[PDB]
Length: 93
Ligand SMILES: COc1ncc(-c2nc3c(n2C(C)C)[C@H](c2ccc(Cl)cc2)N(c2cc(Cl)cn(C)c2=O)C3=O)c(OC)n1
Ligand SMILES: [Cl-]
Image (tube, rainbow, N blue to C red):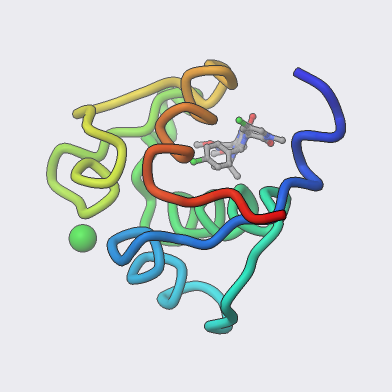
């Protein structure tokens, strides 16, 4: 994964935008750096990870699960995370 990935400018689809609005200000275009941070903040604040197994996010009982299409995932699975995120946005140039 290149460092340039974080510079990608994106327009969230409605479900992603809904989630983002619960953790950050509503603007039209976000960087991937922004999207990752806000989704990360969402996971941390809502305690969707378990303190006894801190790499795994459980989202079966959360909007995030609908966003990503999985009951759980590992925060270490970066390629997978980017794919899950990408399906919820449009890239802009
Ligand atoms: C409890 O302590 C504890 N500490 C730390 C983490 C944690 N590790 C990581 C993350 N976090 C949180 C901000 C969620 C964060 C992340 C952000 C958004 C999502 Cl959708 C999923 C994970 N991420 C990254 C993934 C990618 Cl693809 C790129 N980049 C740049 C990352 O940084 C990680 O590698 C964590 O996760 C539960 N829990
Ligand atoms: Cl929810």
